[PDB]
Amino acid sequence: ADHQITKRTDAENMYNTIQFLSQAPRVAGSPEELKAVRYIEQQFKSYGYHVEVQPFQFEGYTAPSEVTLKIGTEKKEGEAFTYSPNSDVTAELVYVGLGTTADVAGKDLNGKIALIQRGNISFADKVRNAAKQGAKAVIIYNNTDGKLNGTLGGSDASFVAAVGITKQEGDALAANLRAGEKITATVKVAGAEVKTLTSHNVIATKKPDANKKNTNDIIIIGSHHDSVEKAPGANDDASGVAVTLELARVMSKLKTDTELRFITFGAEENGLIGSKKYAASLSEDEIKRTIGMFQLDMVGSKDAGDLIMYTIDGKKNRVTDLGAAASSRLSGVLPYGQEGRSDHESFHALGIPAALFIHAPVEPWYHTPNDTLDKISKEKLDNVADIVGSAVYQAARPGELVIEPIDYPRRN
Amino acid sequence: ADHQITKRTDAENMYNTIQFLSQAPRVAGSPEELKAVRYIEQQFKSYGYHVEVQPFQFEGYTAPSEVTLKIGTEKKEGEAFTYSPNSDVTAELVYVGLGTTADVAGKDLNGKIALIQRGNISFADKVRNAAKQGAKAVIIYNNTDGKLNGTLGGSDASFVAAVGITKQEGDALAANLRAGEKITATVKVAGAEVKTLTSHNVIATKKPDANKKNTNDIIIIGSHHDSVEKAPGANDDASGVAVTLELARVMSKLKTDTELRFITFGAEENGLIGSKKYAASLSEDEIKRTIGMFQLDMVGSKDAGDLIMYTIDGKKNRVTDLGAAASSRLSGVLPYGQEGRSDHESFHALGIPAALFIHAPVEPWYHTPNDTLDKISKEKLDNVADIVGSAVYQAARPGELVIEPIDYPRRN
Ligand SMILES: CC(C)C[C@H](NC(=O)[C@@H](O)[C@H](N)Cc1ccccc1)C(=O)O
Ligand SMILES: CC(C)C[C@H](NC(=O)[C@@H](O)[C@H](N)Cc1ccccc1)C(=O)O
Ligand SMILES: [Zn+2]
Ligand SMILES: [Zn+2]
Ligand SMILES: [Zn+2]
Ligand SMILES: [Zn+2]
Ligand SMILES: [Zn+2]
Ligand SMILES: [Zn+2]
Ligand SMILES: [Zn+2]
Ligand SMILES: [Zn+2]
Ligand SMILES: [Zn+2]
Ligand SMILES: [Zn+2]
Ligand SMILES: [Zn+2]
Ligand SMILES: [Zn+2]
């Protein structure tokens, strides 16, 4: 049965899809994401699918044109968090630890700027905890090497301006504050705006066509079609879109007893928005009948590592059983592990068995301008398509699903 | 053609549905709403429909067990706004007008309680505007006669405790503050909680069955199946559920060229939550093909007035044209007007022509324990079902839709 998939997975199709998509970054809600949506829809229609396009609005952020941070009179290197409010505040700097509700209750922040150490709780909550105490701005300092870029997750008027700074620069400020120094800081953020944008999911469904053998089961194969600002997104996640399209073309050649939904999600990089909107469209019957959701994200880089399957809870489920079974016949041992950070989290949240397929450890080009077509491996793309497609077809081929026992290891 | 609908609308069916549903209030997310969902689903299945149940979560509120308001030492009559945070604050009372961002920028609120006059902006925004300035609680006073009950709309940690008081009691406090008095108040709200609840929409679809005459058009007929706390909800909105079910039974007897979706929405009284969740499930193709959405809310009270159609923008649209055309053949002149406040607002927001059918002015029993079966008129229910069903069938019967010109008046 695996031969029905492996003789048909065309790695030139997949590379051509990445080449098309990665001519420019596809930031969610932008004209280039809309172009991708149209392209994706056309490809599915070309394989014979009826396609639906689900729109959704979300709050986008335009990054501030000025980010001025000063300690006294010395200017410092500052990165505005995404969704940071504007500010122009000069005031006393107060160290409040990790910024928990505990950490901030005891201190006087009204009118002041909070210095807060990265860790434990969300950037969002650190900002809100300080702002609830009257902080006019928040400086968050790193837990680890290099710059602190990040996000408050979404628009929120409980926030006050929030800027991230190096562990080196913050550790030193925190030391001086602990030592009894009174420090004054300036936090000026200007030109940031929140604006409503519209993104989309592209959904192509193959109804079962096996007559008396047809089951009520559904399998979702997903990827996301947006990329981060300035990243061409060839691997993150044109690769997964390309495997999603290619497997829909392959399955169009075959009888199936299981409904397959091939989906590309919008606004993944914004916090899984499009898969949360698609999961919220499902009825209770659809949720109970969905036997697995396969998420393909970063599945073509020559510079990443071996394939792994990640689940939200680090437990095995039907999708990791099918991925391990297909790999054992095609490639070898396929490990699993625990990780979120992609659209499988939206389906796990409904109780649906779900896993992310990704090459790990990831390449250095992730979320950079160097995430480009010249890092793509056709052989990797083909191997992921053979494994994921054979895992899906193990259930979707006509006849009762059987999974034979197979050990496979958890890897961290 | 109208005779295919008017000979079949069974007012005993509709009254029996209200009698079943209104044995107790159906608060969204509660066991009684779940019972209604099951009942509704069963009835549609009994007419031959395939039914889907769309779940959705939302944040529910448990009302505080203590609401203590004092001006100095005198205790006052206070109503917590829905979604009010808890508090226990004794502090200076400061009049801040209507509570706009203007009204509050100039004053010193930090640690204090804001007195704010109802009007112009949402209760929610008045609370957030004051809280952004450091207010520890907000007292909002009425614009008009009687008690001030209301809602901050949804859960929100930007809020601080908010309680509503009479125009009489507030006008007097505002007068004294304007006159230079320094006033101290206490606002104590205790035992309020926000908890995640799950509600549902029930969706029954009749696919077109007219062969070569089939169109691509869709019509939605909606109502909501929840009611407010302590109200049995016979008219608000078991009445509309009963017309929705009855028209689905009627249309099951007839050939149609237009897809009909009969929907009962959950969590309407919480801010249209279920229809917003259902509208968000539609694809762009479904939205473009939906030629009208008919919302039935409060359509059976002996103690309300004549039928009217309300649109969000107070403009005529295809649904008010079809309602006016059917009425002109069945009953007489059917006026339209401008009003929101029901699930048609969720479809208008997508560009879909939508109108609410309701008897106006509404009865005195609205949102009370007296919204009960003994106020229901079978004749009214039958007339709404004849008019709405004939309006829908004017498009859904086989053959090209034709609407003949008809004047009908705007009424305020
Ligand atoms: C919640 C998401 C928006 C989180 C965001 N996700 C992404 O960037 C996804 O495109 C990444 N493909 C997720 C990822 C990266 C590296 C290893 C495993 C998983 C991330 O920061 O990783
Ligand atoms: C946004 C909604 C939750 C608003 C809420 N809506 C409701 O109570 C609906 O059940 C009412 N049926 C709406 C209504 C009442 C009177 C006249 C016209 C329309 C309301 O307060 O009217
Ligand atoms: Zn291969
Ligand atoms: Zn191949
Ligand atoms: Zn669009
Ligand atoms: Zn990705
Ligand atoms: Zn990414
Ligand atoms: Zn090789
Ligand atoms: Zn009649
Ligand atoms: Zn009748
Ligand atoms: Zn449920
Ligand atoms: Zn209602
Ligand atoms: Zn109501
Ligand atoms: Zn009569």
Image: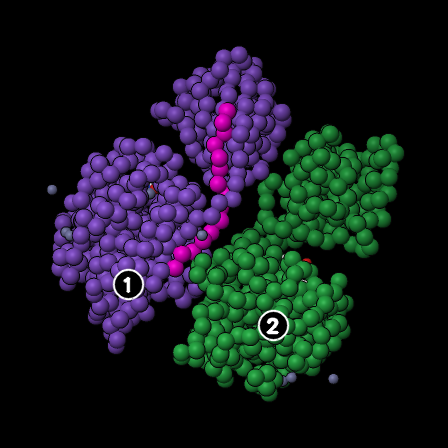
Chain colours: A purple, B green
Mark number for residue A48? 1
Seen from the viewer's position, the closer of residues B316 and B352 is B316
Q: Does any portion of residue B136 appear in the rendered image? A: no
Residue displayed at 50% across by 29% down: A64
Q: Is residue B367 left or right of residue A249?
A: right
**Three-letter amino acid code of the residue under disc 2:** Leu
Write the start and end of the magenta stretch as one range.
Answer: A52-66
Mark 2 neighbour class, 10 Å CA radius: few under 14, some 14 to 19, many 20 or more: many
Residue at (66%, 43%) from the top-left corner? B125
Instruction: Report x, y in % for residue B408.
Output: 70, 70
The answer to whether residue B184 is left or right of residue A216 is right
> Which chain letter goes with mark 1?
A
Which residue bears the numbered disc 2?
A: B322
Q: Residue at x 29, y 55 (%)?
A: A43
Q: Chain of mark 2?
A: B
Residue A217: in sight, yes or no?
yes
- The quadrant of the picture occupied by the C terminus of chain B is bottom right
